[PDB]
Every structure is written in C-alpha cells, then in structure tokens.
Image 1 (cartoon, rainbow, N blue to C red):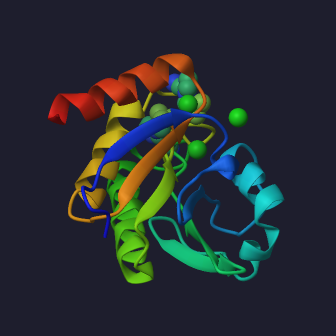
Image 2: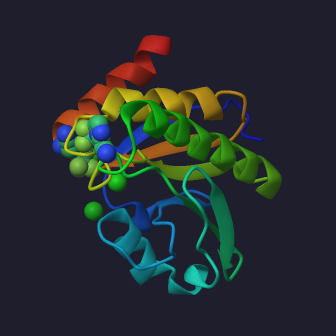
Length: 163
Ligand SMILES: N#CCc1nccn1CC(F)(F)F
Ligand SMILES: N#CCc1nccn1CC(F)(F)F
Ligand SMILES: [Cl-]
Ligand SMILES: [Cl-]
Ligand SMILES: [Cl-]
C-alpha cells in the first residue's frame, strides 16, 4: 500500500504516467479504438492480446511486467441513463478489485465514459464520483489523467473538498 494513500490529478497523456499500472478506457472488443485507448495501444500494444471483455468489467493484461487494466465503461449512446449509470459504477468496482489483486502502490486512471462514450453529455461529476466510490477502500495512490484545462480545475476542486 501507499504510506498515506492520496488522490491527485494531472493534465497530460496517460501513456506518459509515473504510476505502477494503468487503466485503459477500453472498448469491449480489445480494438485499438481512439482517444485514451489509441494512446494506450501505441504505448503498450502487447497488452491487447485477449483483452476483449464485456461492458462493466475490467481485464488485466501484462506488457512485460507493467499491468494494463482494460476497463470497459458503457457507451451512453446505446444504454439508458439508468442502465449506463449501473455499468459505469460496476466497471470502476472491477478496477478496484484488479488494483488490489496486483498489489501495486499506485495506479493511473482516466474518467471512464466521459469522451466518445458520453452520449454528448458532461459526465465529469458522475464518472469521478463512481471512481471515488470504488477506489476509496483501496490503499493505492490514485492519479487521475485528463486533457481539458477546466476539467483539471474541477477534478482538483472535488479532490480538495474531501480534504
Ligand atoms: N462534455 C464533454 C466532453 C468534454 N469536454 C471537455 C472535456 N471533456 C471530456 C472529454 F474530453 F471528452 F473526454
Ligand atoms: N438508446 C439510447 C441511449 C439513450 N437513451 C436515453 C438517453 N440516452 C443516452 C444519451 F442521452 F445519449 F446520453
Ligand atoms: Cl502530454
Ligand atoms: Cl470515453
Ligand atoms: Cl478531459
């Protein structure tokens, strides 16, 4: 575990993370995809061997000894708000199980279902609160990655609010 488990936020490409493992915002088919998933495919392509997994699940594949946790959030274009919310919460619970199983002291994690799977809505708060619900009982240092300047400020505020 980390000596004083923390949350932090950085605005940069998650493929350049300084953590012991990474969470990919994967598609269910283990395809290269776009956005975070394509950056992850370029950096860790070996981790896409048998990475296909259903919505609401996470599947870890090693790239050398570096773990890539493929977490499949729902595409809100296809799910109802209710069913999508349930699958988004479930994907983060499976990430917390994998992080715990791996025994890592730190994890890099993107906000699932906030980009091309958002169904054109702002889901920062919804996705971040499901992240916290899953990760708060873990003792890994969590570093959240984002690309937008206003999102960095909102995520930083949300972390600081809990102290
Ligand atoms: N509503 C929305 C999408 C949005 N705007 C700025 C950042 N984001 C998240 C995203 F970049 F799409 F992943
Ligand atoms: N069939 C479907 C998707 C759906 N139904 C109601 C809301 N949504 C998602 C969206 F509104 F696009 F975010
Ligand atoms: Cl960058
Ligand atoms: Cl997405
Ligand atoms: Cl972002």
